[PDB]
Image (cartoon, coloured by chain):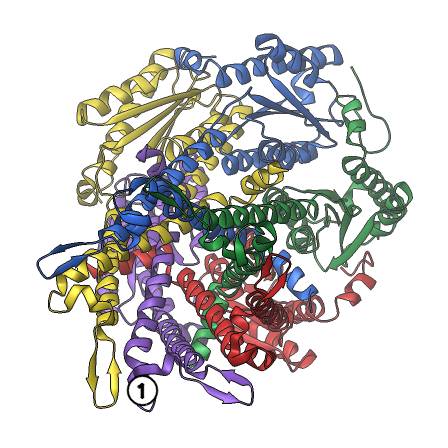
Chain colours: A green, B red, C purple, D yellow, E blue
Amino acid sequence: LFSEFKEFLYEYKVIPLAIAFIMGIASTALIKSFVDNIIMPIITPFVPGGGWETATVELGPIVISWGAFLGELVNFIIIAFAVFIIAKKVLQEEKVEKTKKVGIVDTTFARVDMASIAIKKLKELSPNIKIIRKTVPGIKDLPVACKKLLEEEGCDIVMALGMPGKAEKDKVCAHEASLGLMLAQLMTNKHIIEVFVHEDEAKDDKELDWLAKRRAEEHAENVYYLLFKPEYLTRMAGKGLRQGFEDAGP
Amino acid sequence: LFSEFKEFLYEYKVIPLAIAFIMGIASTALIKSFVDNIIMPIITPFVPGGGWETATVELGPIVISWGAFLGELVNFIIIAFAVFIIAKKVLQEEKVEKTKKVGIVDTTFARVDMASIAIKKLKELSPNIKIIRKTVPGIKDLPVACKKLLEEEGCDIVMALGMPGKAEKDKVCAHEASLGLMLAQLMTNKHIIEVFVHEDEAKDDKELDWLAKRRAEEHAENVYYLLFKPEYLTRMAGKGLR
Amino acid sequence: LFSEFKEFLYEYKVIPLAIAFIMGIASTALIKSFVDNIIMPIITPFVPGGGWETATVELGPIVISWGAFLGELVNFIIIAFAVFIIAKKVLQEEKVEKTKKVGIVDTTFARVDMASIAIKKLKELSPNIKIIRKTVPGIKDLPVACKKLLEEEGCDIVMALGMPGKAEKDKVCAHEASLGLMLAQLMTNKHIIEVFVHEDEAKDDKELDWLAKRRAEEHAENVYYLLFKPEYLTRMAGKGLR
Amino acid sequence: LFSEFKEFLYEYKVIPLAIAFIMGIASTALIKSFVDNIIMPIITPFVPGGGWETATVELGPIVISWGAFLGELVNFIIIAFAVFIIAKKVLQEEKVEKTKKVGIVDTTFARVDMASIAIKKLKELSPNIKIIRKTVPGIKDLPVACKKLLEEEGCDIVMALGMPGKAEKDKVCAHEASLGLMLAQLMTNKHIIEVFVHEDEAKDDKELDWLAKRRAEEHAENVYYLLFKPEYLTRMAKGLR
Amino acid sequence: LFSEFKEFLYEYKVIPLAIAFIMGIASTALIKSFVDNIIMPIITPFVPGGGWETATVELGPIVISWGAFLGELVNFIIIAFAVFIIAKKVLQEEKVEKTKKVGIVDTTFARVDMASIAIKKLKELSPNIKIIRKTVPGIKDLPVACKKLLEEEGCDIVMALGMPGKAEKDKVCAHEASLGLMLAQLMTNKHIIEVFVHEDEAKDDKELDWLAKRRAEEHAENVYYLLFKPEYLTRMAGKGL
């Protein structure tokens, strides 16, 4: 009996559609009721007993019920400002700027913890940033992970920290992963700064740990830049920067 | 000529659009009809015979039909609460969670049955989980499969169990497959825990069967973690679980 | 003068939006017109000459026009059932006992006609299936082709039969193609059973033709399974049926 | 203060939403006004002076204002046909006709002009086809280009003519390109007949030029087939090459 | 309470939906109120005291309230022109062209600054172009970057300047990047002219710098063409280069 309807509404999301009605209808009435019963009589003391409704002026054999129209004209004017004003405030609820929120996604699988450095270095540059952290097991998980923070968690940018293995089985998963991040960003129109450190890039654990931490730091700086002082980057445009050690120019 | 209209509605999904109308209109009237015919008279015994509608007060040459307005003002107030309240309950029935539902997709093609272990180990960790199982022939099929459970079957997460072959012809299908899973996840914003065991990773049938079952178990634990105690994982962050 | 409007409607697809209105409005009126002019008088013979509209009861100085409210209350009840019931029948859209429809896409480029066997074997397993066939020149064309049948031709599943060449130039086009089929499935949430037979998999024309026809058959069976007895497949789960 | 509203409408595209209202409302009224003031009186000469509105029949102590209901019933009927009929005609813009329109996209980069042959051979097979031609610089450009003609230029099918280079640097661009065409088709549900001729497929300029032209011709034929006599292709369902 | 409702509106963006109502309703009324109270009486001086509402003519035992209908007919006519005209002016706001605006995206990572030349050469060919410039660290960042200027910054076309490294680790990122640009273009139906110069394409810093700048220039010329004189490119079609 009742249920089909309820499930029906859920599936087609009709319910919020209808709430527009009620508001449209109800506010339309409240607005005129006010104008007609209170506003108009105040406006028309010259017409007797609030006869504005039937107020009339004759032009030869022409009879124009101006009062009725005037009542509508002033109604419309009052309804207009309501919509003009209701539209302005929905505009400001949008143009505020809350404090940029960064998302950090890392792995259990990962040997070194880059998240730490990164978050530190980010808080340092701008103590005002909000940081959301989430961790997934494998690199295979960064994409969905990031895309979620970006859409569902209101992050403005995200860092994806990963340690693809040394095996060639690991290399394919790393690329494929990276590529997911690509789509992620494109679907969201937001950046996901990728920071992957292959175990094989460094010869031993001492370097692996040092290297990963330096890069993490370096990228965290970019998150800062892209995010706050983008002018800066253009100044460094085509100036041959790089990740650690030597760089380059002309 | 009736038909064109019906198909028309189907194609443009106009029908549910209209149901909003009816509800908007009909609930608007019922709410006021009640206020006007029953509420107001009760509210206004002082006005004679429910004359509230025409109730009026004069201020010098000014005549303000307050009754009518009061009837609307009280109508509006009753309608507002109707909408405030209707909005609150759609917040609780929507926002509130259910017993997490996991999806498990596997293959006929696959040598070893990893679904088993996995489902067991999952029920163990959290006896309260719902499990949907679907099986397709080839690995080429996991994607659509998973994507379906995720969307059509309300699964919160999915495990795709596969056994790509040893041949290089198998390899390409495995990668391509994996890649679809990537997309699937991104299109759904839900995880699909991939668990592929190449026949060549293990030397013989004894290992192949042992190795597959161990991983299936291990990933099933992750499904648990991501799903229930995600805090845990962060604790394990950059801790080199390899 | 008139045109801008028409193009406007086309671009924003406003027209079907509006048909919701008409229906909402017109059905709202017909429902009440009936209730008020016919239903109510029948309901109220006690009130004289259908005075239910103005029917009233006094409680001290209180005057409650219950007739009007009762007419709305009964109206609302009649409109509700209309919407409860209209919602139920749009739910039964999932009749799907109309007969699963399969799509078969093949190539002119292809040496062997796999379509034939496949169609046969399908009609055999389930004489009740509807078969749509479309053919494109190159393998490059299967994707769009399939995705079309899936969406525009109501097929529930599709088989894409192809014969990628022996050349490495062919190998890249085959991979790229397959991958398209990937997306096609993901975008549609329907399966496309891929069945590609590389000219090089078989040593000669006799084998090529034999091999291709066997596979086409074998996959046609799967179309059957996934489509009708999916419980079978799970039974065969992890049974290395490869 | 008028502005916020205007920008507001633009951002949320509310304006066209509203035009639905007006039409819904205005057509609802015009339809009944006609029925009630003109239709009904004609229908009811037996009732005096168009009293159909108040027309009534008694059944014991029951008083049923059938005139009012009948006027709505006949209104609803006239409104139904209007919506049934308005729905039919919106169904017919999307015919299984229109003179088919083909899109041809080529490159400056490309050494040989395949577009020429292709268009000729297409005009030959069916002088009734409309041909849209757009040319981009690099093969990298065909995708967007094609996806455009398909969507924005109402083309039913598109041919993407290209000549990837001999360098392995060229090879990656060609693959990547092709792959773009893939998506293009899938996003549009329309065919893009790819026709790429690698400079290295042919040994010299004489062959390169000949070979490209032949293929271009050959694919053009397919555009024709896929487009007009699709039955034919199924008959060839026969190792053609 | 009040809040749930507010958050509710935010989440489902119901608020702007409703504004359609108000406008639909309010304008419907203002339009008729005008017609009925002022228009009609002017139209009907022959009927006494604005009796047009009840104006009537008999045909035998037929009574047709033509006045009421005429008032709606003329109402509908006035509402129609309102929607016809309202639809026209949203058309001129919808397809008014200022404008062309190009977007330029480059890298810090990149050795040489191509953006400079490109922007010069574009300003030269058409001093009337607007140029938006944004810079990201790595090549991995061009995609999102470009897709942003295209959608969010109203660019009509975008140039993506990059210098993938010499390492094979760099190669893979470059391809992957390029590929992103693919999608980007397809999703937006706008071009992103890619301009990548691998460090290894040139033997030394003198060449690396020269080569990059020349190409940047050359491509910038294409942005011009595709953008302003596209009939030029077709002329150069299949003319190799």
Determine if residue B169 is in view: no
Spot occupied by residue C231 in the image (x, y as percentages of width and height): 41, 76
* Residue name at image x 81 percent, y 27 percent: A232
Foreground residue among E164 and D166: E164
Q: Is residue A67 left or right of residue A236?
A: left
Foreground residue among D71 and B44: B44
Q: Is residue B209 left or right of residue D42?
A: right
Foreground residue among C217 and E122: E122
Q: Where is the C terminus of chain C found, in terms of image quarters? A: bottom left
Vertical side of C199 occupied by B38: above or below: below
Q: Where, by quadrant of the figure, is residue B185 drawn? A: bottom right
Q: Chain of mark 1?
A: C
Which residue is at the far top?
E124
Vertical side of E127 occupied by B47: above or below: below
Badge 1 element:
helix
Q: Is residue C80 left or right of residue A102?
A: left
* Residue name at image x 24 percent, y 49 percent: C113
Q: Is residue B242 left or right of residue D82?
A: right
User: Badge 1: how crowded within 10 Å, few (<14), some, or many (20+)?
Assistant: few
Spot occupied by residue A192 in the image (x, y as percentages of width and height): 70, 44
Amino acid on which disc 1 is placed? Pro
Disc 1 target residue: C48
Vertical side of C77 occupied by E194: above or below: above
Foreground residue among A28 and E50: E50
